[PDB]
Image (cartoon, rainbow over all chains, first blue to last red; front, side, top):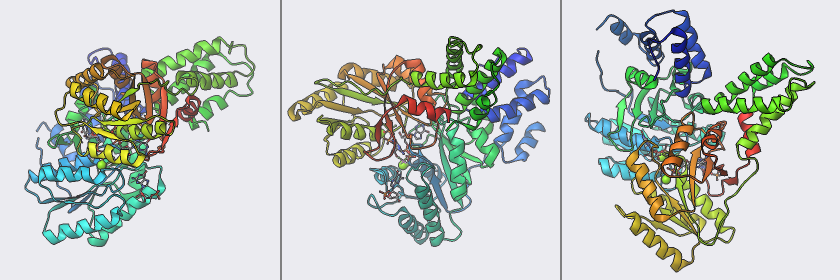
Length: 281
Length: 290
Ligand SMILES: Nc1nc2c(ncn2[C@@H]2O[C@H](COP(=O)(O)OP(=O)(O)O)[C@@H](O)[C@H]2O)c(=O)[nH]1
Ligand SMILES: Nc1nc2c(ncn2[C@@H]2O[C@H](COP(=O)(O)OP(=O)(O)O)[C@@H](O)[C@H]2O)c(=O)[nH]1
Ligand SMILES: Nc1nc2c(ncn2[C@@H]2O[C@H](COP(=O)(O)O)[C@@H](O)[C@H]2O)c(=O)[nH]1
Ligand code: ALF
Ligand code: ALF
Ligand SMILES: [Mg+2]
Ligand SMILES: [Mg+2]
């Protein structure tokens, strides 16, 4: 662990190696260490935690109540009816949509899935299996079908049935492939074509084991489709999801949920403090 | 091709004649930082520049009139070596059974089909084994891929024992005269003891000749810790590096090799069954440094 209560130099030296081992990156680690060094506080533990929690917060009110010595949770509401789920390959987008469905059906919402991975073998069937398990209707087509056309049909079906939420799965794609990014853009427009207000949420899925490439994923997907949120998966692993620090710092996209398993309940709403605690553990 | 940072570090020192030991340490510090930026684990990156230090001094870099050229050459050379030196493919025999192991979603199922197609083209008669019973549609996934590459797929039953698996696989391989058995195992955490135990027991019963750690090129700092655990708890023999068609630098490959010493046999370069290449250490050395 980090030996707090050690001499200043040993504390900062260990904190540097902690953030770097957590995949926080050289740039952001330098940012954090300069200001912890500058603000000169004996309570290094409380000072660092405050700042880290601070990057990972789009909200000073919670910090205000914290520092006033006062604490509340409150379920994550998507802003609209369509949540479009994006990210690279094998990060957990399909598994995460199933968890969201479990999360929102537990809050009493009518949830629909669009099985928009029409590229990968069993890409759609996989979400279909989850729909069956959770008793959630799934809009899917044969492999090779236009996911934009499918996304369109899914919004239309959601609207027709009076459903509250539609999660649109998308095939994993690398951000270096411009044609696949354009296709992603085309899926988004297809959604708005069926309902101009939508999608209100565009959620990036990020695998916690990802190092510095995760920042490039966030920038490139942001540019293409406008992120409104980020989910970090596989946090049940030894990795800390540190690349989130540069992501939130640079892009100001809030972290919505964390994935901590391969089952449908293994989702939690993001907790900046429990995250910073685990990060420095 | 070199990275912005390293273009500066080495550029600084050109034409200056001889350089100081301080100049060396300053340079080696920038190489270290560059490797950490390329996702090389921080202990491994530390050891790597210490290796460079010895070699550069063993080339009498202090007395050289072109020391920046010496330093840069020694980085290119040490990283190539540390990635395996030359391209190396597995040595096959009359009976061949391999596991594909690793973290969740690293590309094991997809890679199995790629290998099946690759070795089919070389006269091998592969058998694919869908051993992932938990991931939804995982057995249909490998079946569809098997059908595409013209290779049979045995699908493990729910709750089936390793002993029963060995039995049906031995049976099908024999009755069909199949000499390359590709076992697709589920992704698992390296700290998940029951599942790491399951994998060790499956190894114990099936006796694979190769155990390939499928590693995603974008994996960060945990690569060292992940490679070590799979190799200590199960025993790895080789590596496949996936998603090199992205722009991750791939420094996790050095971390994995550093702690395991195992060859990196293949690169995955697309989502399609054709997307497989022999791994070239020199090619990734350049990638990491660029
Ligand atoms: N351990 C763990 N595994 C996860 C988590 N989320 C997803 N996975 C696994 O990652 C693998 C790939 O996920 P999948 O949903 O297919 O990825 P997609 O390609 O983005 O749709 C599967 O084995 C999932 O069960 C998580 O939070 N924890
Ligand atoms: N672009 C690219 N994608 C890959 C590569 N290897 C695997 N994938 C993709 O990564 C995702 C996860 O692959 P899968 O084989 O299901 O993961 P597994 O859980 O390890 O079996 C799938 O969408 C694959 O198409 C690769 O070399 N390049
Ligand atoms: N997600 C994903 N989709 C792909 C990939 N390659 C092809 N496709 C799908 O197939 C269409 C084009 O196929 P292609 O003409 O490239 O053979 C693309 O518009 C895309 O939907 C890939 O690597 N990843
Ligand atoms: F395999 Al994916 F999105 F990459 F389902
Ligand atoms: F999702 Al896997 F091996 F991790 F099929
Ligand atoms: Mg999926
Ligand atoms: Mg698989």
